[PDB]
Image: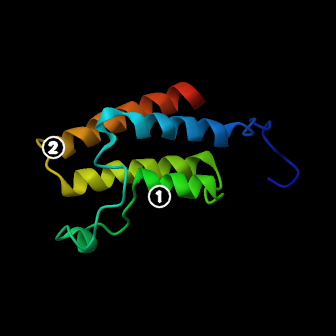
């Protein structure tokens, strides 16, 4: 509350560390469905169904230009990528499996880097 604060967690490395995580996600062999925005002209249904499209290249640009206020807003966009994928893709498809794999990979790196 006013003039009453918990001890200051050091957040000075968060930007660098989210960039490293994002590099590791970008270079994973199963990243290919997620590297670029879904082409809304060429993929029927996507525009109407997926209210907030997100992809690794869009996260990279937001990261690089100070559009994440804190590390939690960064994780919310990474998770959005996988939540969108599960909304649109069957679990038993190459893309569906890719999304599960990547979400697992992300959540481990997130825990090991920050928790």
User: In whole angstroms, how far apart are the C-alphas of marks 2 and 1?
Assistant: 24 Å
Residue 72 appears in view: yes
Q: Secondary structure beneath disc 1?
A: helix
Count all numbered tags in the image, as a single digit.
Answer: 2
- Disc 2 packing (10 Å; few <14; some 14–19; many ≥20): some
Examine the image and state in which quarter residue 54 appears. Answer: bottom left
- Which residue occupies 36% across, 52% down? 81
Seen as rendered, the residue at the extreme right is 3
Seen as rendered, the residue at the extreme left is 92
Residue 99 place in picture, x, y as percent: 28, 42
Q: Secondary structure beneath disc 2?
A: loop
Q: Earlier in the sequence, mark 2 or mark 1?
A: 1
Of badges 2 and 1, nearer the viewer stands 1
Please indicate whether residue 103 sits to the left or right of residue 22 in the image.
left
Q: Nearer the viewer, residue 50 or 25?
A: 25
Residue 38 place in picture, x, y as percent: 30, 61
Q: Nearer the viewer, residue 33 or 79?
A: 33
Q: Nearer the viewer, residue 5 or 45?
A: 45
Q: Is residue 40 above or below residue 75?
A: below
* Residue named by callout 2: 91
Q: Are marks 2 and 1 in contact (CB under 8 Å)?
A: no
Quarter of the image for the C terminus: give it: top right
Residue 18 place in picture, x, y as percent: 58, 40
Q: Nearer the viewer, residue 55 or 3?
A: 55
* Residue named by callout 1: 58
- Which residue occupies 30% across, 56% down? 84
Residue 115 appears in view: no
Q: Tell me, what colour scheme is on the image?
A: rainbow
Please indicate whether residue 30 sits to the left or right of residue 8 in the image.
left
Seen as rendered, the residue at the extreme top is 112
- Which residue occupies 29% across, 37% down? 30
Q: Is residue 93 above or below residue 109?
A: below
């Amino acid at each position: 509350s006013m003039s009453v604060k918990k001890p200051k967690r050091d957040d000075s490395k968060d930007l660098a560390l989210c960039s490293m995580i994002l590099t590791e996600m970008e270079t994973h062999e199963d990243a290919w469905p997620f590297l670029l925005p879904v082409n809304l002209k060429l993929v029927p249904g996507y525009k109407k169904v997926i209210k907030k499209p997100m992809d690794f290249s869009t996260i990279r640009e937001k990261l690089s230009s100070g559009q994440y206020p804190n590390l939690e807003t960064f994780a919310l966009d990474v998770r959005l990528v996988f939540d969108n994928c599960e909304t649109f893709n069957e679990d038993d498809s190459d893309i569906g499996r890719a999304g599960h794999n990547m979400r697992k990979y992300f959540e481990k790196k997130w825990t090991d880097t920050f928790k």
